[PDB]
Image (cartoon, grey):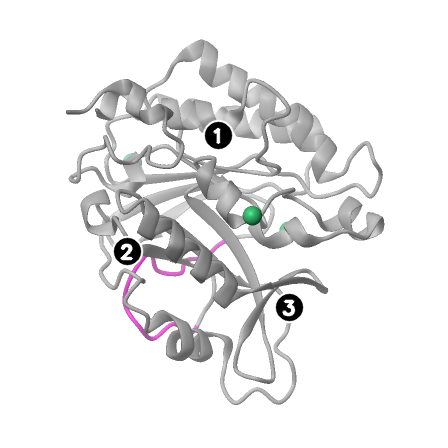
Amino acid sequence: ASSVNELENWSKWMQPIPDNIPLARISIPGTHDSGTFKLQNPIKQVWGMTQEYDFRYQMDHGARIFDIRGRLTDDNTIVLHHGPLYLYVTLHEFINEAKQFLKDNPSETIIMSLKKEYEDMKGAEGSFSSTFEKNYFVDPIFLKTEGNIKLGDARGKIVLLKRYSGSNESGGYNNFYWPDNETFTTTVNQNVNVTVQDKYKVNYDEKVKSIKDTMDETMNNSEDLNHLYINFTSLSSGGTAWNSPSSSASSINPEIANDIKQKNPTRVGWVIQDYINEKWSPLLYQEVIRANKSLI
Ligand SMILES: [Mn+2]
Ligand SMILES: [Mn+2]
Ligand SMILES: [Mn+2]
C-alpha cells in the first residue's frame, strides 16, 4: 500500500503521506524567486538569477512551494519580476504549469506564495489584490478553505500563501506581518503558529548559523502539528561570481543537505532554496523530502 521508497518518486512524493496530516507538518522543498530561470544577460544573472530551470523541472524534482513575485500591468494582468527586472514569465504561465503537473500527479498539491515585487504600472483599473482575485483566484484550481490546511484537502489544488495586503477572498494562508531580513514568529489563520527565517542579507557565516538554528528547533519540535516553519537558505547577491546566488547556493545547499542526511530527522520544515539542480551533492530538496519517512 504505502512504503518509504515511495518518497523517492519526486513527482508523487506526497502520495504516501496520510490525508489527515497538516501541510504545516510536512517537510516541503521550495524554490526562492522561482521565476528567474529565463534570465540570460550575464549582469542580470549575477544579481538576479536564482534558478536555472523552469517550473515543471522544479516540480518534477520535488519542489512543492513556489515563491512568485509579480507586478501589476496596465492591462489587468500580473507578470513576474525580480526587483525592476522583468522575468519574461507571467502569472498565468505559472498557474498553467502547476495545473498540468497537478493533472499528471493528482496526489500532489502546489503551494504558491505571492508577493508584489514592483510598483503597479500607471493606468491599472484595479489594485494588485483585486486584479489577482478577479482574474486568477476565481479559478477552481485554487483552494478556497483555510485553517490548518490538511494534505487531503489540498491534493490536486494550488494553496495560496499571501504576501500581499488588501485580500478580500478566502482560501489558503492569510497575509501576516513579515519583517525584513529577520527570523521571526507570529500567527496565521488564527490557529497556526509560524516561524520564518528570512535573513536574506547577512554575511555567509551568519546565514548558515541561522539556517541550522531554525532547523534545529524544527527537528526537536516534530509533533507540533499546528506550527509552521519556513526556512530560506537563499542569500542575496554580492554582485560578483563568488557571491552570486549561484555561488552561495553551491556551498550552502550541500552543507544543509549533509546535516539532514547525517541526522536523519523526522521533520525539517518548509525549506526554500536557490538553484534546484542535480550538480552539488548531497541534494538539499531530496533530503528534505526523505525526512517525511515517519509520516508514512
Ligand atoms: Mn529576491
Ligand atoms: Mn521545460
Ligand atoms: Mn508551536
The residue depicted at 33 percent of the width and 36 percent of the height is 12
Q: Which residues are magenta?
A: 166-178
Q: Of the numbered discs in the image, which one, if any, rests on residue 118?
A: 3
Residue 254: tell me if it is visible.
Answer: yes
Q: Nearer the viewer, mark 1 or mark 3?
A: 1
Against 261, residue 181 (above or below) is below
Asked if residue 76 lies left or right of residue 149, the reply is right
Q: Which residue is mark 1?
A: 285
Q: Which residue is mark 2?
A: 189
**Looking at the image, which is closer to me, 263 or 166?**
263
Q: Say if the magenta span includes residue 285.
A: no
SS class, disc 1: helix
Which comes before the other along the chain, label 2 or label 1? Answer: 2
Tell me where residue 64 appears, x and y as whole percent: 41, 43
Please state which of the two labelled residues, at mark 2 or mark 1, is closer to the viewer: 1
Q: CA distance from mark 1 to mark 3?
A: 29 Å
- Please tell me in which quarter of the rendered image ligand 3 is found: top left
Specify the amino acid type for callout 2.
Asn
Mark 3 or 2: in front is 3
In this view, the residue in front, 213 or 276, is 276
Q: Dot 1, how many residues are within 10 Å of its Cα: few (below 14), some (14-19), or many (20+)?
A: many
Distance in Å between CA atoms under marks 3 and 2: 26 Å
Q: Report crowding for label 2: few under 14, some 14 to 19, many 20 or more residues within 10 A (C-alpha).
A: some
- Name the side, left or right, on which 54 lies relative to 251: left
The rendered magenta stretch, by its main secondary structure, is classed as loop
Q: Quadrant of the N terminus?
A: top left
Say whether residue 188 is left or right of residue 191.
right
Instruction: Tell me if residue 116 comes above or below residue 260 in the rendering.
Output: below
Q: Are marks 3 and 2 in contact (CB under 8 Å)?
A: no
Q: Is residue 50 left or right of residue 268?
A: right
Residue shown at 39% from the left, 49% from the top: 101
Q: Amino acid at mark 3?
A: Tyr
